[PDB]
Image: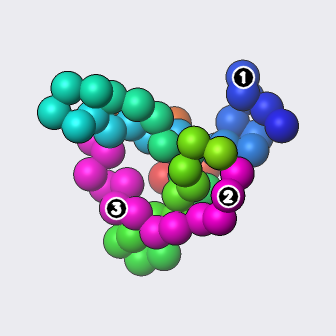
Amino acid sequence: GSTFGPKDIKCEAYYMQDHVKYKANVFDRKGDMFLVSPIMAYGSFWAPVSYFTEGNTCEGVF
């Protein structure tokens, strides 16, 4: 349970929907696909974080 501290986060990427940009927290990777979570702790799904070329916080997976 950490917000200021990428402990439970490690990677937090962004994405905009042509105008609205928000965060997506990312944990690990699987090939060219990454392993992300929604705006809560509920499951985990793969998403191309490679598309989140705005700014992300993943340093330990990099």
**Residue 46, magenta (yes or no):** yes
Q: Secondary structure at mark 1?
A: loop
Measured from the top left, where is residue 41 in percent x and y? 70, 51
Tell me the tag on residue 52.
none
Image: 31 above or below 39: below
Sequence-wise, the earlier of marks 1 and 2 is 1
Amino acid type at mark 3: Pro
The residues bearing labels 2 and 3 have C-alpha atoms spaced at a distance of 18 Å
Residue contact at pointers 2 and 3, CB within 8 angstroms: no
Is residue 53 in sight in this rendering?
yes
Residue at the spot 37% in from the left edge and 54% down from the top edge: 49
Left-right relation of 53 to 49: left
Sequence-wise, the earlier of marks 3 and 1 is 1
Res. 11 image quadrant: top right
Circle 2 residue: 42
Q: Quadrant of the N terminus?
A: top right
Measured from the top left, where is residue 42 in percent x and y? 67, 58
Circle 3 residue: 48
Res. 5 image quadrant: top right
Q: Which region shows up in magenta? A: 41-53
Is residue 59 in sight in this rendering?
no
Image: 55 above or below 47: above
Residue at the spot 32% in from the left edge and 45% down from the top edge: 52
The residues bearing labels 1 and 2 have C-alpha atoms spaced at a distance of 20 Å
Image: 21 above or below 56: above
Q: Residues within 10 Å of mark 2 (few under 14, many from 20)?
A: few
Q: Secondary structure at mark 3?
A: loop
Q: Residue furthest right?
A: 1
Number of numbered tags placed on the structure image = 3
Residue at the spot 39% in from the left edge and 36% down from the top edge: 14
Q: Residue furthest bottom?
A: 31
Q: Nearer the viewer, residue 43 or 32?
A: 43
